[PDB]
């Protein structure tokens, strides 16, 4: 999803800030960990959708396989 | 999986603790990075299973497509 | 992918270093957050490929379902 891409871009922005600050940092590290957690949660949501999409495709292919067996 | 949801909830708990501590913190940030890494590893395991599930569906649909071609 | 496994192993290495340093640490935490972000980005790439793989399987099964309907 574009949100995962948006959360990643925000993590990239915060990462550059934390590295530059390395060269207030602790707050940035904590915020960055929240940025990463949000990304992981968004990826989890899409991953869960693909899991259900795979099971629906499994059901559709099984119905076709059974139709072809039944036609014999 | 429910484990990924459990690892995420633990990361959410540790995140609230680190933010509240921001308002011992370093240990919490290190632990939180382990919580995130465990989540990423669990997501990787489920992602790998979906990759193999997709290839098995590909093989099943290909077998049906070939059966239908062969019947002609 | 093996890259995600390589990024994870690097995060595991950096995590052990940060925990041992807990027992220079800030640089290690920042680097570890970059290791995690890279993992999340790599997982996002594979996740996006599975999403497109699922839609192509959907199109293939739909074509078979339509062929079978049309043959009647």
Image (cartoon, coloured by chain):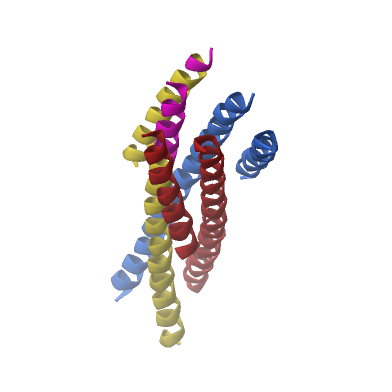
Chain colours: A red, B blue, C yellow
Q: Is residue A11 magenta?
A: no
Q: Which residues are magenta?
A: C21-36
Question: Does residue C57 show up?
Answer: yes
> In this rendering, is residue A22 above or below C25?
below
Q: Main secondary structure of the magenta part?
A: helix
> In this rendering, is residue C66 above or below A43?
below
Q: Residue at x 61, y 45 (%)?
A: B1
Question: Does residue A1 show up?
Answer: no
- Quarter assignment of residue C38: top left
Q: Residue at x 51, y 41 (%)?
A: A28
Seen from the viewer's position, the closer of residues A27 and B62 is A27
Position of residue C10 measured from the top left corner of the image (x, y, whole percent): 37, 29
Seen from the viewer's position, the closer of residues C47 and B25 is B25
Q: Residue at x 64, y 39 (%)?
A: B15
Q: Residue at x 49, y 14 (%)?
A: C20
Seen from the viewer's position, the closer of residues B40 and C66 is B40
Q: Is residue C34 magenta?
A: yes
Position of residue C12 measured from the top left corner of the image (x, y, whole percent): 44, 26
Position of residue C71 measured from the top left corner of the image (x, y, whole percent): 41, 85
Position of residue A60 measured from the top left corner of the image (x, y, whole percent): 52, 67
> In this rendering, is residue C72 above or below A53?
below
Task: Say whether residue A57 is left or right of residue C46.
Answer: right
Number of numbered discs on residues:
0
């Amino acid at each position: 999803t574009s949100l995962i891409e948006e959360l990643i871009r925000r993590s990239e922005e915060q990462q550059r800030r934390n590295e530059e600050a390395l060269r207030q940092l602790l707050s940035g590290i904590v915020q960055q960990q929240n940025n990463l957690l949000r990304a992981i949660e968004a990826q989890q949501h899409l991953l869960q959708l693909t899991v259900w999409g795979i099971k629906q495709l499994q059901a559709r292919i099984l119905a076709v396989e059974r139709y072809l067996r039944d036609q014999q």
